[PDB]
Image (spheres, coloured by chain):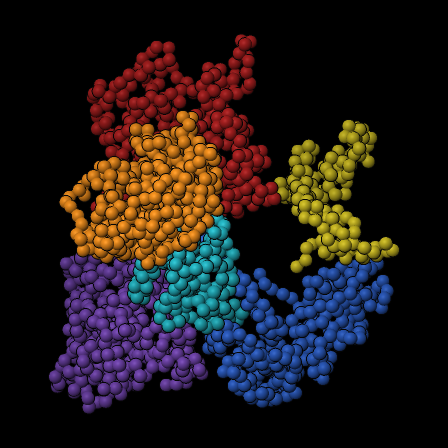
Chain colours: A cyan, B purple, C red, D blue, E yellow, F orange
Amino acid sequence: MTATLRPYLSAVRATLQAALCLENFSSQVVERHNKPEVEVRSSKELLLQPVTISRNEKEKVLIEGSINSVRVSIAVKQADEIEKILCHKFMRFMMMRAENFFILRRKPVEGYDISFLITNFHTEQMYKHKLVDFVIHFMEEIDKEISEMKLSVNARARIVAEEFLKNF
Amino acid sequence: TTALVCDNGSGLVKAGFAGDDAPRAVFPSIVGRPRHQGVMVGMGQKDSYVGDEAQSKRGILTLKYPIEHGIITNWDDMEKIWHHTFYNELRVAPEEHPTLLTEAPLNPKANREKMTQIMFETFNVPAMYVAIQAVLSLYASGRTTGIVLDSGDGVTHNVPIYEGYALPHAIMRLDLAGRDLTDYLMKILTERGYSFVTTAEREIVRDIKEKLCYVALDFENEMATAASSSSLEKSYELPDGQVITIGNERFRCPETLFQPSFIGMESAGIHETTYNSIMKCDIDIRKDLYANNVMSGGTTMYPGIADRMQKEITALAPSTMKIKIIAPPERKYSVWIGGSILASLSTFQQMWITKQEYDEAGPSIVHRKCF
Amino acid sequence: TTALVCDNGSGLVKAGFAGDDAPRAVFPSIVGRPRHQGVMVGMGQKDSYVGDEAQSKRGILTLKYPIEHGIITNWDDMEKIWHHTFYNELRVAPEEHPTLLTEAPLNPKANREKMTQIMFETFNVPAMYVAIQAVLSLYASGRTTGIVLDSGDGVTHNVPIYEGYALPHAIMRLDLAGRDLTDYLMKILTERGYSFVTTAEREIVRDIKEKLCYVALDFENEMATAASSSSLEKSYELPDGQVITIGNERFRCPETLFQPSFIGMESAGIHETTYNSIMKCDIDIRKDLYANNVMSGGTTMYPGIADRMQKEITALAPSTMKIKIIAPPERKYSVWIGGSILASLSTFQQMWITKQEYDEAGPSIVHRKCF
Amino acid sequence: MILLEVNNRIIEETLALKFENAAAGNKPEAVEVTFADFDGVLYHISNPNGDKTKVMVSISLKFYKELQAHGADELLKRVYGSYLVNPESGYNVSLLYDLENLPASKDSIVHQAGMLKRNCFASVFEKYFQFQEEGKEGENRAVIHYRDDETMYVESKKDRVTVVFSTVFKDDDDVVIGKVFMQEFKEGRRASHTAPQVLFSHREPPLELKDTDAAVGDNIGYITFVLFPRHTNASARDNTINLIHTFRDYLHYHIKCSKAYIHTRMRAKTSDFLKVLNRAR
Amino acid sequence: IAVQAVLALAASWTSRQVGERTLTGTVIDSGDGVTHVIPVAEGYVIGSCIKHIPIAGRDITYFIQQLLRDREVGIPPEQSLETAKAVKERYSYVCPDLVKEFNKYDTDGSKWIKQYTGINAISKKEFSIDVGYERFLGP
Amino acid sequence: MAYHSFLVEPISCHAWNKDRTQIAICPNNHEVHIYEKSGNKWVQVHELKEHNGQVTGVDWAPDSNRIVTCGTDRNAYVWTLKGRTWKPTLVILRINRAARCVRWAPNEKKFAVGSGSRVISICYFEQENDWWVCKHIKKPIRSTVLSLDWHPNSVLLAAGSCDFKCRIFSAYIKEVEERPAPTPWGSKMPFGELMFESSSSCGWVHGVCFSANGSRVAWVSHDSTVCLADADKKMAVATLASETLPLLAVTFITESSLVAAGHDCFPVLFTYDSAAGKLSFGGRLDVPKQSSQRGLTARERFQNLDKKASSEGSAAAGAGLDSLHKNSVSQISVLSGGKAKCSQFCTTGMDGGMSIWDVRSLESALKDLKIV
């Protein structure tokens, strides 16, 4: 198994234990309507560090955090058009279904390959750490699914003469 | 850290890493897919149960090991099993680590392109080369020179080596495997009067056989004995609470290696057929070869066969020279471990095609106008 | 709010709502017009009476029961029982929801499309499902591999599963559950001096049975004891202040389940009769299904049953078995209650068959919206 | 279901209706047509000659200049010069079905006249057939630019009738199929145990006409198509010409049919992750 | 991809005699899943004043499938809707008062009391069937 | 010891009469009902709405029964039980946007405040206003208050701020008070003045707590520093940060030991002597109100054909945390025996339940402090 993934995502979840921070405040100088706080960050001392975290040499994460709301973005080794544009027939397909799950910073963001918008609301909405114990790892499983589409698509390459010529 | 070494072949899969003492990634090199209306529809099952899970479910499944023009032909069904390796055995990418692949003698033309098409466009390895499996055995023995038998579940071959220089006309590849045995063997159940005899019981047949079979010591003595005895007959549980007690078949059908002629097949019997390697070989060496007779496979773990085949071979042979016949404990299991340990001679890598060579022309850098 | 869940079949009525622990519509499945002259002005009535109201008027009523071959046959017969059932029993709009109806197989076909013409082109309902009646047990039992029995009154089924795979050759399914043995028991107690018996009292023999009958434990010795002991004999009581006494009949008719052959019925004792179709099948399943057998319906609930049956099933089986006899209290209603759970499953909702399909479709291929 | 005919659904049914109408002596409504097919067609149809009782089909293509150079005309003077007709302007040629050009058995021509497209192609392919039959190498090749990000020619040899190609690759995701699956044709026919030679060539046109390895290690399909006489008999021939007069055009449409399809898997998959995403609870 | 009414604009200038010379007026539109109205002045309009009328010919023709229960018989219940239309459109209209109109059909001959014939497609053989009141009653 | 949610309120704060009987709550949104200790059951006692700015803190003066109410409107009032209901009695301020917290000058003289407007709206009663009025510390402060603690002499004040800089202040008002005793931190003690600071801008100071007499003071930031200032070590200071999940709360429970709690939901102990920077822990304090026998295989089966979170884990034994520690815990307090001799303590959560707890099992030590 890719076992330094264990150091990797155990340290992700140690960061997401050091800093399960996100809790609310509204206003003290400007309006009560809690914002995309990670976008609208004015100043440092109130808030989490801006950060980036390589897995190797192409692969890395960005995380950035207001004390109440957060970005993630994640980068992948793959770089062929046959890796990218083909899975981007899906990453097109993906984004309306982001509207059916509400926490994407809804784009396949470059330098990385994706991004996320995360907030304190969720901490009050249903549950506790089973949440991040799902999320952080589900995020690998949806990568292992690329292997699922891989043999699928490669077998669509195995559609080819298997129709046209095999008619005869 | 690693470079990738496998029994990618027939029987079970028997893979590990470079340099290990043992293959470990191990389950049948065959897989099943539901033969059924899934009447509890939506019960959350994927379309296959694989080797050990195939067996856990074998009453459910359709399964494949294609035409005897090869071992298989839609190798793109090990398609699935490539992932079943990469994740379901391992959770790793081949694309990470230098890979030791393997293939047999005399594969018909298209093999190595059609292979490497996958192995680099798909398995994307840093760099690789492909071995032939015979001398892997001698590596474990710490040897180079003698006659090497394979008989297996894919195939058979019979392989003279001399620190290399192995004989293109006296190495003897053959389609034969334990694969084949059962077609005669299982017709006997109507002699047994069993109104109940199928495809899926072939694995139990093979079981009982792997538990209790042996090759007859001097077969008409055995036939006269079966005609006069039933201590032969030995008991065996069956899955509802039954037993069957059976056991003359247990060495009767184990004559067919000398008698392919049983199906009316015009092939000579085993050692006689094999001798022709030596007959085509150099003649001088045939003294010294008495000490160099190396024998192995899962198919090789039976009782009685050893002394039989020796005396059988001896019916072909002169006396005159000092024998050693050479067949180790675990010879069945062993071959992957010798081939695993080769990679320690890091020299073995330098042959490697990298993905660049494969990219640039194509695997037209190495395929089969190449020798 | 919720969709109705029902034993729309034979037996007792057993109906309620999705998400209930229980039905609340529970009464006799009966059609009950008068015959005697409409006399005492002040009595003032409509034409016919259902189950409880059939009781309430019983001396006056032609009482009838649509359940031919187990089929609750004619449409007019149900329609005002239905009217009652919703509007008056359940006090409910059938239009309020989809509905989880049910069916057994092996009916004549266009039947269902005629029914649907009623259930929509009469009763207009948003949508429905018509779940196959073994399925209902699976939530209730939690089971997925095993044997599913059914015996109340008016249909038998006996279904194998192994994660589904309900077997079209090896299932058993039949025109009635526990019903016409009472004819034999009637043919018995005429012997008890009863020049004094009626049509409307099978319903009451059935009562004495439900109170005092039991499944015989050792029939031959049961008869030896019945032939020799008064200890079997126990009293019963009749509407105007009249005792009777009974005791051997009380197991005699309660042997015909093991001896339909008593009448000359081609069925053996039923679990033997049934065990045969199990023999049409895989060997592996057998201890598993023995360790997984499940019981439901009215007449399944008799005393002495399992402590007889396991020992009679023992008379059939291979050696080394261990058993599970999933025969709960209220097992009769466990099948209703399992449909009440099923209805909650979001996955189960994902193709509720609407009146809106039918509005376009008419009847002409609803049997290929089916399998 | 995905199949086609050389006569057109659009045309046959309407004009057989016009000829049902011609048999009835019926009065017009305003038809004029232009449209396209495979092979770069400009179809046309009309109410020609102004009046109440004529119809004319017409057709125009640039590379007609490469084709009128060849004696296609004579078979067509049989099959269709059975009918009485004249070229229209702007079109290369036209069929006047004047309603007084119609026979007693008005149906019988309709199929034939509609199938004319491929049949014009066959009317000249017969010359390379005749060259092969006369035992002739290299004869009188029909170099046509039907397409031009592509190339073709028809030619002959004594054993075998021939066509050759070029076509420029646009995307590597195409090339990765192109330089693989036809090499499981050029090395794979056991389950399709019929085919003539077809050589898709990721770089390689044949030598009398262009020359081999004329592409970017893979970026131009110089496909080639050559017939065994188990095709060049007066029969197995026809089946096959039909396929060819659509093949890669039709294929490159099937590509997109199949592109669409995967979104079943993807619908299922993406819906699955929408299920999976709940499980954080 | 234009809004469907954009095609109908061309018909309003296919009609093109004198006075066809501005974009101010009012279309009334109707159909089978949809009906529409639109306050166009030189192309401009107002949201809640444009009208999107959901009421349409589907919604009629199944109501007409219930009018079968008034008079007529012998049909597969999905050739039922087919036949219902195959009557409807040539014969149906409006009356000024119901209670006048009953009596024409009750009395005054086949100009009211027409009859229609067709096929029971249960196995493709005839039915001959009523017409009358259902004409003025439908629209 | 014991727990129940009689109804599942997001108890965003809690407050009481000093006999801990009538539970007032910060609710969801702008909708309050007070409940009461019906023996140990919980039953409604009031409906309140007219402080319409949701709710934030309060200061229920719990003897006198005067809930000074706060939140997202200047309809901020002493709610008092008028016999009928708790009902408003207005405060006048010069804050804006909100009030987060409010704080009686301990002898109930007045209260201190934390504004939606960078400021301490130092608020003082007028019989002449019929109500409170204020004056403002807009400067020398820079930004507003999350937590508050008067030193026991009641005109002397500590706070935790969104201006970060860990500052000690005076806020005497001439028209209600007189200036306090020579404060060793600093003794310029009029209105708005600064006594002392620890240079710590180190997170927004989130909890502030005097020792059992306030001879030393602790602080924590929500960035989860844990810290002190001690006067008798000659205006000494200390700072540390936790290992564990980020803070909900901290309190002294002596002059030498403290209870802390964070997004780990369990409380942890702290311990100390007088060794300046020697801040030290004492480990997790609680034991769960659950044991492993929980289960119902029938619904586990029904909803393994359906699949919502249907792959199990003991995280679910705390609705994601494990430890029965829920979607989240939300507050802590001592019930009785106090920051010296506690007999019982309690906690709230997102689940809406009362909980009360195993204290005196941990009584097992003697004396504290060392002048270091």
Residue D68 quadrant: bottom right
Number of marks in the rendered image: 0
Judge left or right: residue E69 versus residue B216. Answer: right
The picture places residue D171, in percent across and down from the top left corner, at 53, 74
Quarter in which the C terminus of chain B is drawn: bottom left
For the residue pair D58 and A102, the one nearer the viewer reads as: A102
Q: Residue furthest bottom?
A: B284
Quarter in which the N terminus of chain B is drawn: bottom left
For the residue pair C223 and D92, the one nearer the viewer reads as: D92
For the residue pair D236 and C208, the one nearer the viewer reads as: C208
Judge left or right: residue F324 versus residue B220. Answer: right
**Vertical arrangement, residue F324 with respect to residue A48, above or below:** above
Residue F224 quadrant: bottom left
Residue C240 visible in the shown view? yes
The picture places residue B352, in percent across and down from the top left corner, at 34, 81
Residue D225 quadrant: bottom right
- Name the residue rendered at 64%, 88% in the picture: D139
- Name the residue rendered at 32%, 74% in the picture: B97
**Vertical arrangement, residue F156 with respect to residue C27, above or below:** below
**Vertical arrangement, residue C205 with respect to residue A156, above or below:** above
- Name the residue rendered at 24%, 69% in the picture: B23
For the residue pair F367 and D216, the one nearer the viewer reads as: F367
Judge left or right: residue F212 versus residue A161. Answer: left
The picture places residue B241, in percent across and down from the top left corner, at 23, 49
Q: Residue furthest right?
A: E18
The picture places residue C317, in percent across and down from the top left corner, at 26, 43
- Name the residue rendered at 46%, 34% in the picture: F128
